[PDB]
Amino acid sequence: PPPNPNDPAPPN
Amino acid sequence: DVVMTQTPLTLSVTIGQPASISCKSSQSLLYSDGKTYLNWLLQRPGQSPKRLISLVSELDSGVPDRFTGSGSGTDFTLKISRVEAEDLGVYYCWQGTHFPRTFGGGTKLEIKRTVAAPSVFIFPPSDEQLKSGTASVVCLLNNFYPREAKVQWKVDNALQSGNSQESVTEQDSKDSTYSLSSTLTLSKADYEKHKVYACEVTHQGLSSPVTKSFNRGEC
Amino acid sequence: AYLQQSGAELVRSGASVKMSCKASGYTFTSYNMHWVKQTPGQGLEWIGYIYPGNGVTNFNQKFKGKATLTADTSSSTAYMQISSLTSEDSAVYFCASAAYWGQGTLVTVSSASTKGPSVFPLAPSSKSTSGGTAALGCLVKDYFPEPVTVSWNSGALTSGVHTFPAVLQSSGLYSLSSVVTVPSSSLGTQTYICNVNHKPSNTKVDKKVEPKSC
């Protein structure tokens, strides 16, 4: 399973 | 900025003891996607941090199930069901919901264990260094507990001051002990003025002080 | 998976430094790549991130216009450039993404010339035996700045090693010891070589540690 994020990715 | 307050500052625990660390944020960590971005890290000295938990409660792959994370809003907790020797280090929480990203101040987890006496060793200066005009003598105290130890240098039975430096390792992740290295440094001219070089070690695991010594030229 | 950072740097006041973070074992473009400062003895301070999927950056206001963050997706490598360095910028710098942290890059801001270490044996003898074991080591003396790396037997020896924190000598140069405990029985058949690397001076030294007769 891919790791969970630390924090949300930014929008594009 | 959102401030992350961690308590306690230090946890002193025995093997097998449960442990709990609190992280409180100054503002809610709920993000607009419904997730709460709260991470826990463990750092060992001279090593990098390692992530243990993300999204408040989700253990990373390979992290033992003795670790659990809980909380919501502003109040978060990392618990260890039973502490093992390898759990020592500095724990940090950090929040991923707000800008700037911010970290707690850290909680240092240290292991208490039985008293262990040092193994004591001494090393004369090398011919290579003597050729350069200096003499360093090293006294080594290996794998002792607690960290407090006294090293006294003596030269022809005269107590030295002012010509030595020492340093202590971090606590060991397997046996929870410390080690210490002390270096006495003299010019070659001063070194050759004396015969007996000794280090005397006092430690709670020793029934009386231990002296290691050598005679210059013989050793 | 892993993040591999570039080696330690000595840089002059007012100059700039560029360091790298090579990623493997997770999707580099799917997670923010963070950079984090640690002054030794202290906590962690966030500098900024780049998201490699689209290049977007976000910074701590303290570091805006000081730090530049980039990401090369063809090589899965992130970079941080810090400009106008001052004494307060000497620190370890980490990259961090997904479940991983890099091992840190130590930056020393100083106008002093680099100096490589001298390496002296800590020879085993009847005065360095305890309970049938023997200790031996290397004294790594008179270098600047930190760090040195010490391995033993080209990395084939790791058990029983203590590489101590360096001390600062009154000359302003560092000194450290690295020691190992081994069987006394095999000092005549085994070879012990300490391998010392000091990147800022491009110095490598291998020193064979042989027993004393005493």
Image (tube, coloured by chain):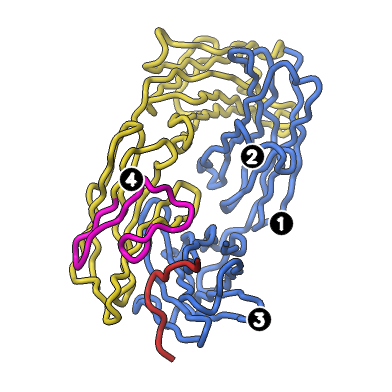
Chain colours: A red, B yellow, C blue
Amino acid on which disc 4 is placed: Lys
Q: Quadrant of the C terminus of chain B?
A: top right
Q: Position of residue C119 (x, y in %)?
A: 69, 38
Distance from disc 2 to disc 1, alpha carbons, whole Å, reads 15 Å
Whether discs 4 and 2 lie on one chain: the answer is no
Label annotation for residue C140: 2
* Image side of residue B67 versus residue B193, left or right: left
In the rendered structure, which disc, 2 or 1, sits on the residue that comes first in sequence?
2
- Whether residue B67 is situated above or below residue B205 in the rendered picture: below
Of circles 4 and 2, the one toward us is 4
Amino acid on which disc 1 is placed: Asn
Q: Which residue is mark 4?
A: B108
Disc 2: which chain?
C
Distance from disc 1 to disc 4, alpha carbons, whole Å, reads 36 Å
Distance from disc 3 to disc 1, alpha carbons, whole Å, reads 29 Å
Distance from disc 4 to disc 2, alpha carbons, whole Å, reads 30 Å
Distance from disc 3 to disc 4, alpha carbons, whole Å, reads 40 Å
Of circles 3 and 1, the one toward us is 3
Q: Secondary structure at mark 3?
A: loop
Q: Which residue is mark 3?
A: C74
Q: Quadrant of the N terminus of chain B?
A: bottom left
Of circles 3 and 2, the one toward us is 3
Label annotation for residue C202: 1
Q: Secondary structure at mark 2?
A: strand
In the rendered structure, which disc, 3 or 1, sits on the residue that comes first in sequence?
3
Amino acid on which disc 2 is placed: Val
Instruction: Count all numbered tags in the image, as a single digit.
Output: 4
- Circle 3 residues within 10 Å: few <14, some 14–19, many ≥20: few
